[PDB]
Image (tube, coloured by chain):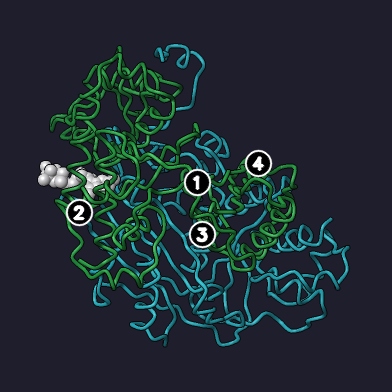
Chain colours: A green, B cyan
């Protein structure tokens, strides 16, 4: 288990400890994680490798830091002439009907990027462009720079040349001001702010995957329906962050068997956060009246315009009748 | 208005003219497109615009290139220290349990990439890697570079570290020898290899999108079923390239209305090219016995293991009976 993999595993343990109760990101937290799960590589190795986020704060506590994590401490302008190029979908292979391209200033945190999403519509392509950036930046100059890079990157499509700065949805993130932060439900709550920063959940080995599913059910179990009706919107969004990540780890039969949807306190969470949950298999609706429902284009019922049927356990008599079609 | 929009439309004019009539890619072809889509900007601003493909060939002709396009002239190793990142799903958010990443050398043509597709299965992670590259490359050494970049990029390098070069499928494309090419159905036919080089289809504006769709239908309409059975494989694959792009532009209702699938000669295209077509909305199967079928996990038919049901147009009286559920 290298130094990175151990760093990954300690971050897993902090995320898992965030499920049952909020915890301030400070060295004691990392210390409790090291109990059942120590750091076995050398501290000298750790002084070499460079990581970011909470794994860097794990590294610094392993290297003796006694102060708590300070929101905004990672701030960085990035290199204005080094760009990162990433994309999902293409015009020839779009994904869920869309293709999206994001170009950003390398090593910028918060990340200063221009994302251009596109789809085929009647009359050609519609584009939706988002400039994710920081308060006070030269937005127009930034846009015009990242736009050029989009044009040069994708062989100058007409559709991108047509996007004006006035077409661009601008999102200004604030840098922290050094607020201490609380980790709860895989999300950071900076003290003094109302927003959260959702963190990557991790938990990709079998053991931590099974722990994550266990802890979430127990966490919800540890709330009364009144407890849920009292939570701030920010903790609810935090819980949403974890719930949706868990259900993407199940097929429909496992998800229903998991049983989190059957709990009273979770029904109160469904009223505040929504009933529609993607899974590994498709999408379920945990409805308070109809029961468990499953996405189904042949559905006689609709939930927020999603066609659904009653999810029932797949039994072999339905599949024996599946008509194999001539090629 | 502008030079980029003009270049695109000269490029669209070639792609569109190629649907019905094959033509050598040489400067006289761009001359005759300039009749319908002139170039009003100055050659001096033309010289800053960086393009590839036919867009760059047009630019070169406008700047006075009088030689014909030579297959393989765009071949470039790329920068082995600059990388592009394509992802389809995520370890945090997989798509139907899968996530795929492709990392490639920036500006490599043919593209040299390593594609790792990964799934969460019972217990661990199954990976499949493909190295798409060029005849003659240092395959192992390219794999090890691209695998490193995949380890640095991954939210889960543990599952990547175990993939060995013996586990990786290699596809090698060949570079051209300077052959002249014919453009037909948006594809280059080098004289006289047996393969084609599919070209990107632009047509991002109202005029060229609508005409792209009417020409493809006109092309098929003006072949009988006997004409289609006499098409070589390379011409079948070119038609396939225009058919599949066109159907990515419609939702399912629009794809069906377009009616290309009702032409008897298209039924012969279907037998020879496949029945499964991706649209903007779903996957459709143009079946010869059952009609238009739509991918449907809960369908009672299967086409080549694809679960499907009969596609059904929205009818207001039926939509009126859909039980709208309470939120
Ligand atoms: C680590 N895991 C595990 N997992 C899901 O959880 C299951 C893993 O297999 P498993 O349930 O542990 O096997 P097991 O219960 O012992 O036997 P069975 O075959 O009956 O399920 C799979 O259905 C897989 O989709 C995951 N799903 C997502 N989205 N991300 C993840 O990191 C993980």
Chain to which mark 4 belongs: A
Point out which mark residue A169 bears.
4
| Alpha carbon separation for disc pair 2 and 4 | 44 Å
Point out which mark residue A178 bears.
1
Residue at 33% of width from left, 25% of height from top? Answer: A285
| Alpha carbon separation for disc pair 2 and 3 | 35 Å
- Is the residue at mark 1 in contact range of ligand 1, meaning its CB lies under 8 Å from it? no
| Alpha carbon separation for disc pair 3 and 4 | 19 Å
Q: Earlier in the sequence, mark 2 or mark 1?
A: 2
Q: Are marks 2 and 3 on the same chain?
A: yes
- Residue B218 location (% of width, % of height): 64, 50
Q: Secondary structure at mark 4?
A: strand
Q: Secondary structure at mark 1?
A: loop
Q: Which residue is mark 3?
A: A86
Crowd class of label 1 (few under 14; some 14 to 19; many from 20; radius 10 Å):
few
- The front one of B109 and B240 is B109
Chain to which mark 2 belongs: A
| Residue A269 placement, left or right of A178 | left
């Amino acid at each position: 288990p290298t130094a990175v993999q151990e760093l990954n595993r300690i971050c897993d343990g902090m995320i898992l400890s965030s499920i049952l109760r909020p915890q301030m990101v400070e060295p004691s937290l990392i210390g409790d994680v090291l109990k059942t799960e120590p750091f076995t590589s050398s501290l000298e190795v750790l002084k070499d490798i460079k990581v970011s986020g909470l794994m860097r704060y794990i590294k610094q506590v392993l290297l003796g830091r006694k102060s708590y994590y300070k929101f905004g401490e990672e701030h960085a302008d990035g290199d204005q002439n080094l760009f990162d190029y990433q994309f999902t979908g293409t015009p020839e292979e779009p994904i869920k009907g869309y293709w999206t391209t994001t170009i950003s200033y390398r090593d910028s945190k918060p990340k200063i990027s221009l994302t251009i999403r596109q789809e085929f519509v009647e009359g050609g392509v519609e584009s939706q462009a988002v400039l994710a950036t920081v308060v006070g930046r030269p937005h127009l100059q930034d846009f015009l720079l990242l736009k050029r890079k989009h044009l040069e990157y994708s062989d100058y499509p007409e559709s991108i040349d047509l996007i004006e700065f006035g077409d661009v949805k601008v999102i200004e993130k604030t840098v922290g001001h050094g607020q201490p932060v609380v980790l709860y439900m895989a999300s950071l709550f900076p003290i003094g702010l109302t927003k959260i920063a959702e963190q990557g959940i991790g938990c990709h080995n079998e053991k931590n995957d099974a722990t994550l599913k266990s802890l979430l059910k127990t966490a919800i179990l540890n709330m009364t329906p009144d407890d849920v009706s009292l939570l701030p919107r920010s903790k609810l969004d935090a819980i949403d962050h974890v719930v949706r990540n868990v259900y993407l780890r199940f097929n429909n039969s496992s998800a229903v068997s998991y049983g989190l949807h059957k709990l009273q306190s979770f029904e109160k969470i469904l009223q505040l956060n929504g009933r529609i949950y993607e899974t590994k298999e498709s999408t379920l609706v945990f409805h308070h009246k109809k029961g468990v429902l499953v996405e189904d284009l042949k559905g006689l019922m609709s939930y927020k315009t999603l066609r659904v049927s009653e999810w029932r356990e797949k039994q072999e008599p339905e599949e024996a009748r599946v008509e194999v079609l001539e090629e």
